[PDB]
Image (cartoon, coloured by chain):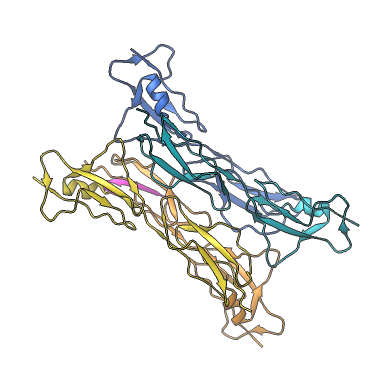
Chain colours: A yellow, B cyan, C blue, D orange
Amino acid sequence: TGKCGPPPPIDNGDITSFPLSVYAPASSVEYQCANLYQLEGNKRITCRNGQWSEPPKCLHPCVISREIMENYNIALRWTAKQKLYSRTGESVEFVCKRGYRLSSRSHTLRTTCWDGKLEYPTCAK
Amino acid sequence: TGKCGPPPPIDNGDITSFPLSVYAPASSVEYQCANLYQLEGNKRITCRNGQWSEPPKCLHPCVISREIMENYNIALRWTAKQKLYSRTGESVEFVCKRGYRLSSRSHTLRTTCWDGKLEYPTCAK
Amino acid sequence: TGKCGPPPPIDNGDITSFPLSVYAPASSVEYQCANLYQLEGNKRITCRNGQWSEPPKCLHPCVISREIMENYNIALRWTAKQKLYSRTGESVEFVCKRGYRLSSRSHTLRTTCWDGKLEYPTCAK
Amino acid sequence: TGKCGPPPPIDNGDITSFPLSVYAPASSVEYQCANLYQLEGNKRITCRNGQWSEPPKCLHPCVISREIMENYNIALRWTAKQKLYSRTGESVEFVCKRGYRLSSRSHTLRTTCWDGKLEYPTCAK
């Protein structure tokens, strides 16, 4: 008859309803990700044939690295608008520090967070 | 020119992006409510003329009361599906305990959570 | 015999264990407050004589107001260390904007967040 | 001089203060884990010589599996006290279903959650 047990926990996310001990086939619940995490895919899982469908993934935000920025000779462009943490899919804009210019082959000064990873621009004297 | 400061915190909710010190007019951010809380209204606030628009409200879940249920001679209908906490808008179904029947003027056995409040059915011997 | 039902939800906080439908006298659970909220009092509630003891309170963080700061002619002292949100009990330090000085009877430039409220210093030309 | 950047995010946890763009050596922040997650080790990280110390780990709760329980011929012992999710370090107690008894070499009926893993008892007809 295909009933399911309690829905699976996922990293950095939670279901939006109170977990029950058993669910009828065709039942569904939904996830939400922790605030700065981006929910990837379909938020809803459905019970069918004794198994829940695949939960979504909560994609990681990116944190600025002081060490990397110092090494690459860059700084945040907007000191009044500092995205110290950025959501996946969200862009962060840097500038070369005074006395430096973009190196060749460097990434653009504007760069996009993807699941924890920022590819930083590099500046050279 | 109408810039705004950091978005206002709301009870039982958070914005989905990292707060900035200043926002240009027309900028917007969005809220999400804590997992069992229901977001009422529009999740997005927009900055215009120096003020953020009105944030949404996170409506409270309902918790079952043992004392009230004992007093009213009721129990949860489905012992395998116990909604100890219910979301606003979600219904909970009771039954009269063995030897009792609904009193007249009683609420229906099925009853809906609204922002923390459940109106309980009452059974009589 | 004094058993208790599911522990009460509190604003901006959650219990650290999975809620059960019934608790024996002497049982206890504990709360934690949402990240920037300060837990006031004892985090643990205990079941006795059919009632849970009093839960703690989650004290609100304070958010900086651009409008108030502009009106009072002040700015954050440390632009590299901007406490846009401060925890209850945590202090925030302002400076008079260029061309202003503290007014008499003004609060000190350093001021402490208490449950959502900051008493701002005031500067005059 | 050894200043640090914004503290690192950790899975299933958050810092308790608002992130700053730079921290002086000797500064510290603290983490808390999401509600059913158990914080392993020291909650506080300290900035020294340009690096944060190692953050704690948030150990996973365990979810009961209907499929595994059905296969092993077991059920939760206390239907009024169902730990559908258990914290790391917390124990869950099963019983053999009617008509079964513990198999030899089986784990005890009482078993402890560790970071997502429950070792289930097994019953045989």
Residue A89 lies in the magenta stretch: no
Q: Please report the residue visible at 39 percent of the width from the left and 24 percent of the height from the top.
A: C69
Q: How many marks?
A: 0
Using the rendered image of the protein, determine whether residue D37 is visible from the camera's viewpoint.
Answer: no
Image position of B37 (left or right of C7): left
| In this view, B47 is above or below A24 | above
Helix, strand or loop: magenta stretch = strand
* Percent x, y of residue A1: 64, 79
* Percent x, y of residue B73: 83, 56
Q: Nearer the viewer, residue B38 or D71?
A: B38
Image position of C98 (left or right of C41): left
Q: Please report the residue visible at 71 percent of the width from the left and 64 percent of the height from the top.
A: D80
In which quadrant of the rendered image does the N terminus of chain B lie? top left
In the displayed image of the protein, which residue is found farthest to the bottom? D125
In which quadrant of the rendered image does the C terminus of chain B lie? bottom right
* Percent x, y of residue B122: 83, 53
* Percent x, y of residue B59: 60, 45
In the displayed image of the protein, which residue is found farthest to the left? A125
| In this view, C75 is above or below C40 | above
Q: Quadrant of residue D27?
A: top left
In the displayed image of the protein, which residue is found farthest to the right? B125
Using the rendered image of the protein, determine whether residue A76 is visible from the camera's viewpoint.
Answer: yes
Q: Nearer the viewer, residue B94 or D72?
A: B94
Q: Magenta residues, as a range?
A: D43-51
| In this view, C18 is above or below B10 | below
